[PDB]
Amino acid sequence: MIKEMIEDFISKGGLIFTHSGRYTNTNNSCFIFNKNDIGVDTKVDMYTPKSAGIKNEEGENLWQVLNKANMFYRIYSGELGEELQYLLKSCCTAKEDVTTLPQIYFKNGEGYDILVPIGNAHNLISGTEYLWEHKYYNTFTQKLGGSNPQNCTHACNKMRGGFKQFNCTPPQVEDNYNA
Amino acid sequence: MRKFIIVKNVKVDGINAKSSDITVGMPPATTFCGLGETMSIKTGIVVKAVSYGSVKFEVRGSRFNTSVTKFAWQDRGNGGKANNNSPIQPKPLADGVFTLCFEVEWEDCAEVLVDKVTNFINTARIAGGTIASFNKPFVKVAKDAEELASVKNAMMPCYVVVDCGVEVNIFEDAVNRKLQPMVNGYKKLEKIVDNKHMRDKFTPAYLATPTYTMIGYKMVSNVDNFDQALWQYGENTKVKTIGGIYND
Amino acid sequence: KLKAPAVLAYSRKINPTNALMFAVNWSDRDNTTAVMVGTKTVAGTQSVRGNPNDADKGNIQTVNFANLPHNKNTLLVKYNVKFVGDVFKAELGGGEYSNTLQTALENTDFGTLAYRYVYNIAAGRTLWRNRVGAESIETVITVNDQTFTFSDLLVNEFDEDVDVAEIADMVAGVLSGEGFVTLKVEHYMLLGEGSEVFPSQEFVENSKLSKQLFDLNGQAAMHDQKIGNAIRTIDTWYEDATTPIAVEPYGSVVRNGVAYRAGNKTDLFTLMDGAVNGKSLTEEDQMFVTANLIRGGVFGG
Amino acid sequence: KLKAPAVLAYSRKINPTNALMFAVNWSDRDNTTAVMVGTKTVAGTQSVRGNPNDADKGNIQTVNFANLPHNKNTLLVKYNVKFVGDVFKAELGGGEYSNTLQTALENTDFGTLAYRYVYNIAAGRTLWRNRVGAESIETVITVNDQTFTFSDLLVNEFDEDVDVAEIADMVAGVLSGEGFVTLKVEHYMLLGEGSEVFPSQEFVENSKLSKQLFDLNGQAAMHDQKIGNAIRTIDTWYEDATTPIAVEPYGSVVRNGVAYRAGNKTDLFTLMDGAVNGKSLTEEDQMFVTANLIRGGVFGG
DNA sequence: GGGACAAAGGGCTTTCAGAGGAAACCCATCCG
């Protein structure tokens, strides 16, 4: 029920990641995995060319299957055995790509460090799902990909409604009065 | 807390409203700290802390679905299909008017600083925007904590950002505490090995992700301690305020 | 072979601002009145190609508008421009390619580029479709406490003028290495009482409105990108198509669907590669490459 | 085959303004006073088809009104009209389709169109239902410092006149490639003391008021698109049904619910597509296409 | 002249996938 989809993923050039820069520019191909951020309710993302895959009999992809009821932590820890544990961990490989990314100088004691900011995959999905049901009507809505959003990520392909962003508009000084 | 310089009613157009993947609006305190560091390195004058207040701000567009800026063909991979409506890669823009306070350590004179600041401001940027106009800078002198209220009140009128800290995380705190998140620093993930495409081959390179903290907006006349409204670089790649967590 | 770097970037050397609109009289241009936007609702028919059996139904739309009041008959558009130097300074990369390009260049004539950039403002091309319907357009330009007034016609076919030279020579000095200069521009027109004005639009996802106009705290304004686009419409240096277009790499007009400077051995990148690899270019080619390098952007692939 | 481009649009070449309503005397038309709107509350019965059980209940409504003062007996409606040229110049797209369409046209006679456009204003069709109940209607047209006075009846059945031709000759020259021309139009009525006037309503959602009228600073006015609709009611060139209608693709009247020029080989898009593909059009078809191009719209898909 | 590699460019393209969803906030002082 789960293994066949794992051979499906490893057959293509798929990758598992928690942070990536593809959320800022579609042409980016930078994928890295963080092990210290894995928890009970940590959402992860995956990338395969054209996001084709094969759906289940009821119809599900890996992004939905692993992020439904926290079977990712149920497998990463090894509660389902050591057969589905090594294969999944084999996909967690870094991939460096800095073309078309921001680069900023930051003060680090005596000297400077150049940094390339990238976005986190867990935060977008977690915030969208948590905030859609709490009625927080002080947010924007952004859609990635465009006319064909199936070539950016797996989360964008399935979450076609659009990710949510905080509206950080500050109060403004009203004129024609004291303040 | 000795010498302060005030520049009020600065008009900037085309500010990059996208500070992170989930924050759209005011630039974080990191942008103003970097502007102060750039002023210090270019001008040769040591700057201690920076304070910013929002006079006006507006994100282009509507209540939701802010805006999209049209793109153009500018890469060397096309020429045949580069004739109709290049892809988007969204990038929001906004327009705002701010007020800035800079802590300066300079005692050579009193009027040279105004000229040297005005020289740098005429050719500077704020989060990628273009400065339209600004008022003449003036310098205030503080000898003790009691007269810090006067230099604080010299910044009227504007809304200053104060730090309140995070309890659990920004998502739960925003719904419950009713505050807005902000970026205060970056966390390093892994070191860059290939140094070919980087803008500098001497500075070490890192992959970083933003760290979020919750802030609040307060009137200048309602600030208890002025040291809570000044930001500066901290430890472990963070930006922190002198007064710590703001408490009423 | 001196292969170009993977990513090459340059800054923008011309900085415009958001234009502001006011309503004044032709003889009382001292006191100004702001122009609001407002919202209206219109009704009509459905005329869409390919749908003939649905043409007997109605159509209700909600739009924005902007027009002068019935007691004012003059539109005033005011803005500022900044010209800065430090050309041939790459923002990302370039240690030998940029120096070779700089050495190959700097022999071009910046006087023509400075004349054309100032003429696009003086003649009145910076203001869009608000131009039509006006019997008199007056331009007031201020720089270094020295004002000039223009009533120049013939926006196309750049011709020799006496007053534009005193600004073109200053801009030429700034372009080939100097500090910064600032020009304050004001435009007066004679559209009439109640005439409709055309501020900038926006591309926004579907909302309660069908056409939303740009504004700044309830006052109609224009985007800085729109102001800057009209300034650099000087590309006259190709084979045909008089009434020139804006200078862009692979110079194309997406509105018209046509792309000049196509794959016929006249591109920005082809000329840039050929200039550093030995043989120099003609006057028109360097004048185009330098003008395009004045415009910012990142080149790579 | 020369298919039409995906994006293709034209701007508007006839620009009217919002009409202003004043109350004056028939022999003292120098001094004018505004016409306010106000609000009233009325009571009536419930007469709705299909509900005879609730026919004995009351009905309280609130509406707006507008009527002349009891000491004035003349209504004055004033506005301005602007005609601009540069026809056959597409705003969006068109490098081969627009040029071929312009080549196929421009052989038509602009004289009839310029005559009818001016006649629809002079005969008094721009002023709507306010016409009824008046025994004397006067029209004053000012252009090029030359005044013209009209008292012509028979709004329909275009006849020959000597004063309409002089203005129509100026309009026709501007239409076939020129700058702009402007007309000042004033209409005088003879309704009588205390008579009711009919300004333009507004499309409003659910609210307290059942009928609110368009007003500018509390003064009654008329929408400019309503004024422009009556100017271009010249489409007499279809098979029957004299007393023509306005020119529109798939020429339809939503008020009557019928749609002329349906899918029976008489469309704007069909004729425009066939004109460039070999066979030309007739005189009436060329005049219809030119008239529909003077009016704006989108043609592509 | 034939074989291999890389780059650039175009075109034959074309492969890939897919319907959620509901609502106007933060906040009152210096100065002539």
Image (cartoon, coloured by chain):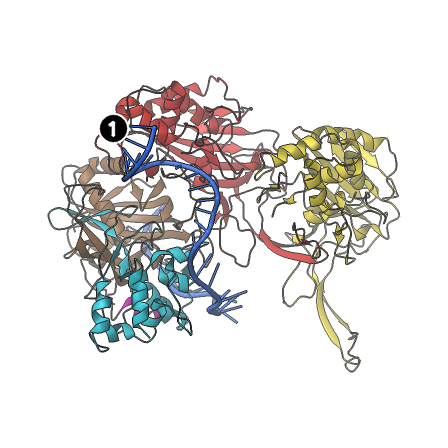
Chain colours: A cyan, B brown, C red, D yellow, E blue
- Left or right placement of residue C73 versus residue D44 in this view: left
Q: Where the C terminus of chain C falls, by quadrant?
A: top left
Number of numbered tags placed on the structure image: 1
Foreground residue among D234 and C101: C101
Q: Residue at x 82, y 44 (%)?
A: D236
- Left or right placement of residue B213 versus residue D214 in this view: left
Q: Quadrant of residue C289 in the image? A: top left
Location of residue D78 in the rendering, given as x and y in whole percent from the top left corner: 73, 43
- Magenta segment: does it hold B169? yes
Q: Please rate how many residues cluster around mark 1, counting C-alpha atoms within 10 Å: few if below 14, some from 14 to 19, many from 20.
A: few
Location of residue B217 in the rendering, given as x and y in whole percent from the top left corner: 32, 60
Location of residue B75 in the rendering, given as x and y in whole percent from the top left corner: 36, 39
Whether residue B60 can be seen here: yes
Whether residue B172 can be seen here: no
Q: Residue at x 50, y 19 (%)?
A: C159
Location of residue C179 in the rendering, given as x and y in whole percent from the top left corner: 29, 29
- Left or right placement of residue D236 versus residue B193 in this view: right
Q: Where the N terminus of chain C falls, by quadrant?
A: top left
Please, what is the three-letter code of the amino acid marked with disc 1? Lys
Q: Residue at x 76, y 32 (%)?
A: D110
Q: Secondary structure at mark 1?
A: loop
Q: Relative to C165, does residue C76 appear above or below in the rendering?
A: below
Foreground residue among B150 and C120: C120
Q: Relative to C90, does residue A88 appear above or below in the rendering?
A: below
- Magenta segment: does it hold B216? no
Q: Which residue is mark 1?
A: C1
Q: Quadrant of residue C143 in the image? A: top left
Q: Chain of mark 1?
A: C
Foreground residue among C288 and A4: A4
In this picture, which residue range is highlighted in magenta?
Answer: B163-175
